[PDB]
Image 1: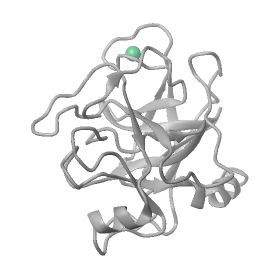
Image 2 (image 1 turned 180 degrees about the vertical axis):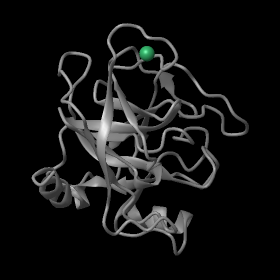
Image 3 (image 1 turned 120 degrees about the vertical axis):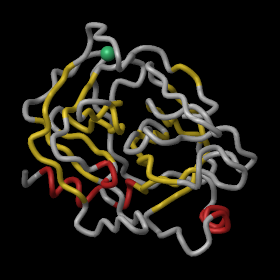
Length: 223
Ligand SMILES: [Ca+2]
């Protein structure tokens, strides 16, 4: 997250870190057994880390649970990132508590203009590289479809939305991929892509989770 703030330990209790020997992507706990992330964060051998604040110190509220299954969307296209969503099943259910909690899936899609909370352990520099240890947060508004398509001509599908600041300076970034965009208390986006991070006229692009709720529900009903 570039231009964000330190969230505060366990104040984003549905945020997970995906670990394959190191943190590589975020995700969102949607019930005790399932995490939603980005399909471009697929790796074999994922361990889900819940209750994290500092990802490099065991502070006492973590649960580390191996994934048993990952399910990339059936229509994921890794070239365009259309349908950039994946489900990860935990080998064992998380113990839900004040620091490890699920986020609701949406009933309706979020509105342009809505300020959402984006979080993660990704890079905090627009130019250069610095990865935080503790979870960072950003409030960013959803941008109109026409603004998003003007920023990325011929690249935005109906399964993507933009959020952020066209003047630059505030955005998600590498290493935040897969993590949540929460708007009015529901998971509305997944950190997916953008041109650089926090560059002028190049806002973040997010997977539109409200288009996937039927797939998520039927998949979790089946696995
Ligand atoms: Ca930790």
